[PDB]
Image (cartoon, rainbow, N blue to C red):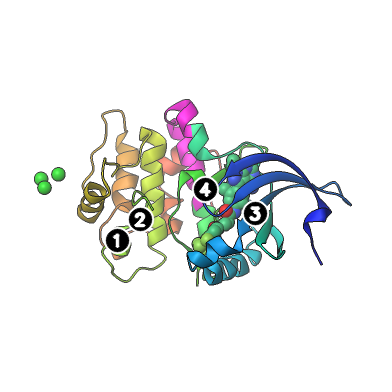
């Protein structure tokens, strides 16, 4: 029992491939939220309508302060609407390009929030695909939120080798994801960035990257342990949260 006339639409927060995201206020309650608009024909011409459905299905069952809330959804004749938690402080992507790179304390805190969220997802038998900084939003107290759905049960920069090599993948993709982001947070660009898709593919498959001099031994150690070609050599999240560099630098308590 939901419709577009139920919401006052504010400014565009952002414009995406399959549609746009708007600030919105629910009329009866005055609840401020983010309304994401998707056009059916687009999703269909891309054949991802079913996948969207599955991801939204899995999202509904996810309650965690570091995961964007999905309040509900509906559709008219031509569009699909996702009613989402409004994240007032924008994306990590935008923060990174304003600050150039993050210090070790912001980085370890962000990694901790992600590991906690992912750890909660793992317990619910949920794993995440690609994790990109444009898909990490910031709450009012600047807490990080995983904002893209899917959730299992484009640029290659954030894909693990097993995914680009066409091998079997599991929850270990999440550990790779933390490794890539930890590096990007500290350095200001992901560790396999390149001018072409072709070069990036090679560099990921090879795990061919280097650290700038300013990256500390503690951070190199964590990143080197996450970015293992063999998914089975990657640590458990439980061990990311107890890493001495994480422990020494992060403001956020581990797990729960
Ligand atoms: C980043 C962000 C994400 C989301 N949720 C999604 O995007 C889920 C959709 C999805 O995963 C999907 C879509 C199509 C598709 F085909 C498939 C497939 F094929 F895989 F099935 C999957 C809602 C709001 C925002 C958001 N963005 N922003 C910026 C504009 C600052 C914001 N500023 C403030 N508050 C905000 N909430 C936001
Ligand atoms: Cl070569
Ligand atoms: Cl080379
Ligand atoms: Cl070479």
Q: Secondary structure at mark 1?
A: helix
Residue at 51% x, 58% y is 118
Q: Secondary structure at mark 4?
A: helix
Q: Nearer the viewer, mark 2 or mark 3?
A: 3
Name the residue that disc number 2 marks.
159
Q: Is residue 176 left or right of residue 132?
A: left
Q: Nearer the viewer, mark 3 or mark 1?
A: 3
Q: Is residue 112 above or below residue 126?
A: above
Q: Is residue 100 visible?
A: yes
Residue at 42% x, 30% y is 101
Q: Earlier in the sequence, mark 3 or mark 4?
A: 3
Q: Is residue 214 left or right of residue 186?
A: left
Q: CA distance from mark 1 to mark 4?
A: 20 Å
Name the residue that disc number 3 marks.
37
Percent position (x, y) of residue 58?
59, 68
Residue range corresponding to the magenta coloring: 96-114
Q: Earlier in the sequence, mark 2 or mark 3?
A: 3
Q: Is residue 212 above or below residue 234?
A: above
Cβ–Cβ under 8 Å for marks 3 and 4: no
Q: CA distance from mark 2 to mark 1?
A: 7 Å
Q: Nearer the viewer, mark 3 or mark 4?
A: 3
Quadrant, the C terminus = bottom right
Q: CA distance from mark 2 to mark 4?
A: 14 Å
Please tell me whether the stretch drawn in magenta is mainly helix, strand or loop. Answer: helix
Any mark on residue 164, and which? 1
Q: Earlier in the sequence, mark 1 or mark 4?
A: 4
């Amino acid at each position: 029992q939901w419709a577009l006339e139920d919401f006052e639409i504010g400014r565009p927060l952002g414009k995406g491939k399959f549609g746009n995201v708007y600030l919105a206020r629910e009329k009866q309650s005055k609840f401020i939220l983010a309304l994401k608009v998707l056009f059916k024909a687009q999703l269909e011409k891309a054949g991802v309508e079913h996948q969207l459905r599955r991801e939204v299905e899995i999202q509904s069952h996810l309650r965690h302060p570091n995961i964007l809330r999905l309040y509900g959804y509906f559709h008219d004749a031509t569009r699909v609407y996702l009613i989402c938690e409004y994240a007032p402080l924008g994306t990590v992507y935008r923060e990174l390009q304003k600050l150039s790179k993050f210090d070790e304390q912001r980085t370890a805190t962000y990694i901790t929030e992600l590991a906690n969220a992912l750890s909660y997802c793992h317990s619910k038998r949920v794993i995440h695909r690609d994790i990109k900084p444009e898909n990490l939003l910031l709450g009012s107290a600047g807490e990080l939120k995983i904002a893209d759905f899917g959730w299992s049960v484009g640029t290659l920069d954030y894909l693990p080798p097993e995914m680009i090599e066409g091998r079997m993948h599991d929850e270990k993709v999440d550990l790779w994801s933390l490794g890539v982001l930890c590096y990007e947070f500290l350095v200001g660009k992901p560790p396999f960035e390149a001018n072409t898709y072709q070069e990036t593919y090679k560099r990921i498959s090879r795990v061919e990257f280097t650290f700038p001099d300013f990256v500390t031994e503690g951070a190199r150690d964590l990143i080197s342990r996450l970015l293992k070609h063999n998914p089975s050599q990657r640590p458990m999240l439980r061990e990311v949260l107890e890493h001495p560099w994480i422990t020494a630098n992060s403001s956020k308590p581990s797990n729960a």
